[PDB]
Length: 171
Length: 171
Image (cartoon, rainbow over all chains, first blue to last red; front, top):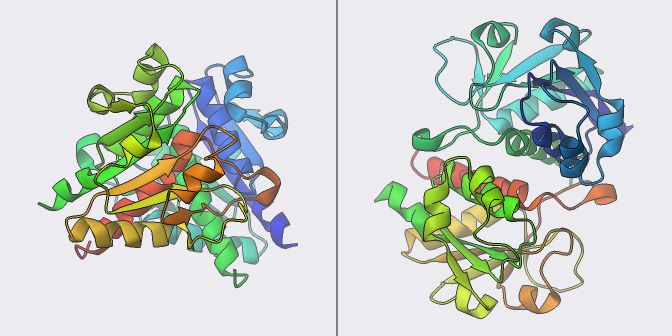
């Protein structure tokens, strides 16, 4: 199963401070066909704001796994891609969201499990967290005002994943 | 000017009910280089929630024009593109976000002014509002759970606009 492939994209939110962003991320995942959410040390979860921003994606919140470390969140993944909003001076392969989606599909088609890792509001992932990833993904943005809202960033990546998944089906 | 071209994309939010979405839209515009926001009959504006979700894109909120009708919001535009989340049974040309961005760039390069029109949370634009547009833009989504958060939808379209704008510059 085709739609079922999308369940093997593991969205990992690292140390999210605003519970509204957890809900927003779940909504962004559900409206692209994704469903697997993992939270590393969220600051406030469960929370009413996550439920409200999920706007019906409460199934994803209820099935979300909450873990103490990024290592636990990445267990069993065939590849890990971390997002970066700025030059991090780490020489890892740097992908745009379209290239990220191509890499994701390649793994999903090979029965892999892909982690897409998002960091804290503003600060992003730490260097150590980025070093744990095999690829870095950057959403091209205005360098004068470069970091997107966490849920909006999840939406951009999940949208590209769905665009690649549709294209592979001749759709 | 190149960056200046993006100021000629007019983001129009029609009858927004959650002020947080107005702020989220302004943030989504600013981190892609856009700045022109027009609000048609927003339910609560100005509002603290718009300021909070703008996360520093308060300049866009302060310069936003508030009007009573969609007609006033579209004055002087060379083309109007409206978003749709479902089959609207209106036979207008239907573009995905990449095709929307191509159309936008074509107009910006020809010193045009493009309106990107977003509707109400859940309900979207009315048929009459969609009929006022020359093109309809649909973000491919899971038809089981098809409508994105308003600010996340603005982010998807603005992200594609920036991707097209960068590509045209050999970047």
